Image 1 (cartoon, rainbow over the protein chains, first blue to last red):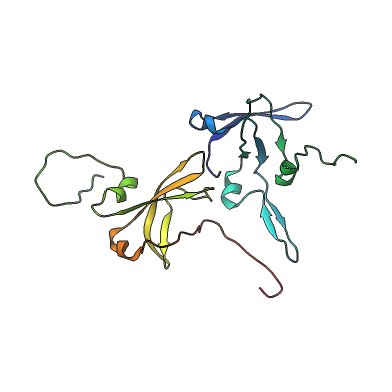
Image 2: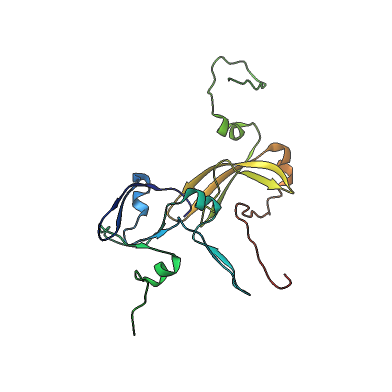
Length: 103
Length: 103
C-alpha cells in the first residue's frame, strides 16, 4: 500500500532460476495474510494508444526505489514458497507462464 | 543547535525538548487533522500542504493500518482562519498526462 514493510535479504542463482529470500518486520507481520501475491516493481511499462495510454510497473519514486509490491489477501496459512509474477496482468490472471494454456 | 522560543506565563526551570519534526505540532495554536486514504500515493512525513500555491502546512506523520493509510497533518495558525472546514484534500504527489487529438 505504498509503505515499506520489508526488505529483500539475499538473492541466489540456481539451475532452475532465481530464489529471493526476503524478510517482513514484525510490526506488519499480522498484515501479511499469507494467501497473498508478490509483483515485480523494478521495471516500468508504458503503453500508448488512441484512447488508452497507461504507465504501469513503477512510478518515478517506485522506479528510484524498486523492489517488490505485495498484494495482500484475506485468509491463509502462510505457506513457505511463493511465486513471483512478471507484471500486473499476469498476477491478476494468475498465469505464471508466458504462453497461455490451450483450450 | 538549541533554539529558544519565548512565551508568557509563570516562570519555570524545567523543559521538555521536542525534535524539529514535531516543532509545528507543539505550537500554541495549530490545526491538527487526520485524513484516511486507501493508498499512500507516495506521500511521506515531510511533505507540505499547499493552498492556492502557497505552503500553509506540513504532513506530520503517516501510519499504516489494516483498513488503509492514515495521515496526521498540521496547519499553521496564521492560515487557520482560511481552512474553512467544509473543504477537500487532493493528492499532489503523482503526475497525470492525458493525450488526445484535441484534449
